[PDB]
Amino acid sequence: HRPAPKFEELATEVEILETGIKVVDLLAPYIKGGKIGLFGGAGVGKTVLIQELIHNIAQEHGGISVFAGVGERTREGNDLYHEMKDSGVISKTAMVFGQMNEPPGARMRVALTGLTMAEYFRDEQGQDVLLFIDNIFRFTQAGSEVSALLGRMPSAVGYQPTLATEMGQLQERITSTAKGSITSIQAIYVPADDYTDPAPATTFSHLDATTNLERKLAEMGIYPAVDPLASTSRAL
Amino acid sequence: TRGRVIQVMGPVVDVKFENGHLPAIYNALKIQHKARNENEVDIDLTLEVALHLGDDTVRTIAMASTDGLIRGMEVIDTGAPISVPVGEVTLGRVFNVLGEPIDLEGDIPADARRDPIHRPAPKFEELATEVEILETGIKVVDLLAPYIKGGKIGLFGGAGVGKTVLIQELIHNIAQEHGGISVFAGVGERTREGNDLYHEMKDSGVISKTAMVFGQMNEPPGARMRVALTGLTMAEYFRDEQGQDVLLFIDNIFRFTQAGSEVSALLGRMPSAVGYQPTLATEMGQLQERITSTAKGSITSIQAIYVPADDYTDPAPATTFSHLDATTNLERKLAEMGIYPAVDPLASTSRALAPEIVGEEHYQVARKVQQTLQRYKELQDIIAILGMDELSDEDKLVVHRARRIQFFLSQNFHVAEQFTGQPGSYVPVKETVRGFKEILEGKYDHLPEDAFRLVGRIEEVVEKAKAMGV
Amino acid sequence: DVGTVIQVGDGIARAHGLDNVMSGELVEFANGVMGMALNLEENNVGIVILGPYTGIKEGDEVRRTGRIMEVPVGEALIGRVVNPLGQPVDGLGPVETTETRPIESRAPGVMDRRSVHEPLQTGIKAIDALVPIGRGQRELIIGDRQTGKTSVAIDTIINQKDQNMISIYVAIGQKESTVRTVVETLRKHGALDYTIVVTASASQPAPLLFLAPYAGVAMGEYFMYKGKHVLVVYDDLSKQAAAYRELSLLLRRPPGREAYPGDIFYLHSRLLERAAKLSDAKGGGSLTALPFVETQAGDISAYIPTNVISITDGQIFLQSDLFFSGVRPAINAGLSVSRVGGAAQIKAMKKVAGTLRLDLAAYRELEAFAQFGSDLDKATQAKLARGARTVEVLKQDLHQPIPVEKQVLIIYALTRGFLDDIPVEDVRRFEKEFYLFLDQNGQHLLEHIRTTKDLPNEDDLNKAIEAFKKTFVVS
Ligand SMILES: Nc1ncnc2c1ncn2[C@@H]1O[C@H](COP(=O)(O)OP(=O)(O)OP(=O)(O)O)[C@@H](O)[C@H]1O
Ligand SMILES: Nc1ncnc2c1ncn2[C@@H]1O[C@H](COP(=O)(O)OP(=O)(O)O)[C@@H](O)[C@H]1O
Ligand SMILES: [Mg+2]
Ligand SMILES: [Mg+2]
């Protein structure tokens, strides 16, 4: 827990990040220091995309990366660990896990500890760190559960009274100063195919580029399942 | 007596005075304070008691910002509900809720009459049997949807379709031909209307009699609540003391429920319905029931009301709508046609005279008018799809007469004299019915349709057609 | 007058003592963080924290200040970026305090105002020609997310270089990097000569978020009362509304219709009524405001949009489908109206821009039908051609406000039918080449437009546009 960076420190320059994926590179470029969101339903390949992007970045760009699992499936965490170990990428990256069977407070704070790892890397080593976050949806849910336990009155769709603030903090400590970018790629699940739940909207307000995955493409022969028209980046 | 402040809770205020002999509910307390040192701030505030608590505490509501209130400051109680100044001296100026004029032209003397706002409604003994129709001098209103005096009128008209012109004409007529004065009390947006009313009703002089009361959105909840009751106390003075044949007007009812939306924020108690105060029906009823006819004096407090909410099933519009007596609608499409006032055949109640008393001719004429208009509407639907020329002769004659009937509805308002240049015409209800009857009877089928515009009587239509050099 | 903090949590503390505290008075702790006293119980005070509350511990000493929520104002603030509490944010040393004023003052009342008759130029052809705005008017801007709200506001502030105005930009809950980007974009074009930027980013506590627009309007009100015209833009009122909701919920007040309490209409209407056009008796100041409201899925019908739209004098609606399709900017005539407009608009534009509205609406309906059905009548085809050219004229590129005179001249050229011959894509080239030609040949027309405020000599204007057609080369 540390006070945020100030206004005078921040830089404004724009640098594109190359991923090597045809759809992403062509129609939705990602930006150093910017926050990139992955939206979609279940079983469409968001985790496959993020894992293969981690591998590709470590293979070609060679930059440090940090992975934060907010309430990840133990089976998926173990499979990811084995896959990265086989890939020879683990040595370049770092991972922190907050397991589902833990009290909601730990599942809330795990993203912040991952951010602190990237913070020290960017402040002392002064290079282009990346931060991958498994799912912000469970972060918001853990915040709601902690608020309910503490005795605060609910709001919106059962959500905690202080939601916008916590999301804002978690996504505003991730800023590209002159020294280092701390680019982030984040995945979010749409509960009922409606882009109106408070967590997706609050995260939607904060994104520079959004890539949304469709189940129809996933069940088609077209891999990856990225809808061209609805995916946009402000750096196009 | 004297009591000290102990608690402050912002808008609900919740000042818990510790006192010797408590004031009754709705009583007024006034706070006077001076800047003894650099830190303290001078404040002069009025509060209304709303609830008694344990021991000596009496909850209150403040009518202005409470910034600068300090525990321990002394408070004095007046002895009666907040006293509006009312009477001849107060006529002809714009007031706040408490009773001071906002425009600094003059200050009301201390000697003036001051009356409490909160009064029980007239007893059942003093009421009167209500069968009569108030004359408006507007052909369409006197032909399709007459107004029962003493009853609440509804007009669902968007801003900019003639609301201001219609109300100016109504108050001008009611002050010209009747002994009635009007009272206006707004809550919403900007009062540009002040200069329009200044022009026309000060040329007429009625501005000197209409005692407008204003407190709008920028005010705290308490004033926004009590503004309408101040406006009503203005009428209550005339009806009780003056007892003239003044069938006065008050021009806002629903705006009290629009303020009641904020009274839900004023409560600070258990919610009910859709967030509304539990006492919605009772709180609105207390206001609505003070508007009555009486045998004490020939004063009917008939009111024309605009409902901004315009949502049918919502609890507050429904509760307000249950009290309404007559309804009218202003629509922009009719304004396009140049037919003014832009009122359509929609009506409500108003059968106390026709056909209840005798009202045979009036009722049959109105029914034929509405039937002909709906037939013309369906015929117009048919005309666009296929073409008028293929219609039969007997069916074509209906459109032929319908054009004249549609155009005759326009009235050359008196208030329009300063823009149009037309002196303006006033029509008695019986004259409206008698003259219009011939139109349905086809006395003037041969006359050109364009003659039937902005004229008071049928003979004027005939002479205008003649002036067209037929 | 000393006290101790007896409770702390999520920004709402409590304190014991403070006999002489005044409701609303600024209070401070040994740490140095500022607090706003809000509730005074019989023996303890409820304090809202403005700053980092982590450092506070129960048992901390708290000291009253003696001021009632005063925000410093002065001439020094021009060109700076400051916090709602008035603290410097961008370094550059401490700002000089001319005077300090509270933020809870009463709005300008009835019978102290005047009808709006003075234009305010945004620089966008579509807005200036179809939906004019007047000084002292409040015009709300709504659209789907990522539709150019901030681009339009920056275009207005940039165009306000010529006409005397003190512009104040309030960033509520906006991302800090975007705030700094806008600050630098205003540093270029010289917009920081007069503009003041007030920022309270997402990281800031909710009390600061809800307090920011009040502080900005309070700062503008001083230049209002001295007589200077002001233009204040709120980047997003929805952040203020949400931050209000959160504070009330933490204070345990029951919610209203939605999670929002019943106060929000009072809270936002008290803010918006503070902008007024003053009369000669009060100095004749003015404060235009252009609030922004976020819309999900392009659905206007919602609690916040209707609640605020009931307050303003009009609104402009931007559609994302048209914007992304390539029509930038994009405004819908059906939902966009300005009730105060027409009196501020200069007579030249009122005369020039009569048939443009009808052409736009009728052509758009006919184009919908035509894309539905191929076969058409000749008159409908001519109307389609005219509407196509009209659509082409209305297009405007980024960060280039156009002076009014070129607008009225190009609209005249469009409406008279001189432009009809030019092909679709060549229309924009025609427009900029015509601007260059106007700079080259017809200066007296421009000066007569400036001085007269009315259309210049029509014959010479016809000759000039005909000469430009004679010089212009198609394709
Ligand atoms: N007339 C125009 N032509 C071309 N591009 C434009 C035009 N107007 C705006 N844009 C572009 O569209 C984008 C609008 O971004 P902007 O920040 O203004 O969006 P916004 O709708 O205000 O959203 P948000 O509230 O999230 O900030 C920018 O990339 C800007 O360059
Ligand atoms: N690009 C791809 N190549 C191969 N298989 C894929 C691909 N995308 C999706 N799949 C299939 O779908 C599943 C994706 O799982 P996951 O990425 O966890 O989905 P989600 O992110 O929606 O939970 C995989 O088990 C795989 O069988
Ligand atoms: Mg997945
Ligand atoms: Mg923007």
Image (cartoon, coloured by chain):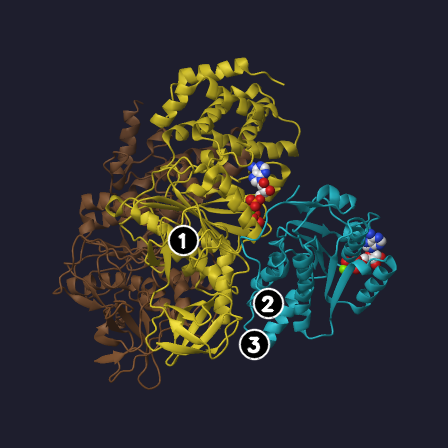
> For numbered disc 2, what is the local secondary structure?
loop
Label 1: chain letter = C
Front residue of A88/A217: it is A88
Q: Quadrant of residue C280?
A: top left
Q: Is the Cβ of the residue at disc 3 closer than 8 Å to that at disc 1?
A: no
The image shows a total of numbered marks equal to 3
> For numbered disc 1, what is the local secondary structure?
loop
Q: Is residue B368 visible?
A: no
Residue count near mark 2 (Cα–Cα under 10 Å), binned few <14, some 14–19, many ≥20: some
Q: Which residue is mark 3?
A: A151
Say whether disc 2 or disc 3 marks the residue closer to the N-terminus.
3
Chain A: give its colour: cyan
Check disc 3 and give the amino acid type.
Gly
Check disc 1 and give the amino acid type.
Val
Q: Which residue is mark 2?
A: A159
> For numbered disc 3, what is the local secondary structure?
loop
Residue count near mark 3 (Cα–Cα under 10 Å), binned few <14, some 14–19, many ≥20: few
Front residue of B336/C293: it is C293
Query: Which residue is rendered at x = 21% and y = 80% of the image?
Result: B1
Chain B: give its colour: brown
In percent of width and height, residue B328 lies at 38, 51
Whole-angstrom CA distance, mark 3 to mark 1, is 43 Å
**Where in the image, quadrant-wise, is ligand 3 located?**
bottom right
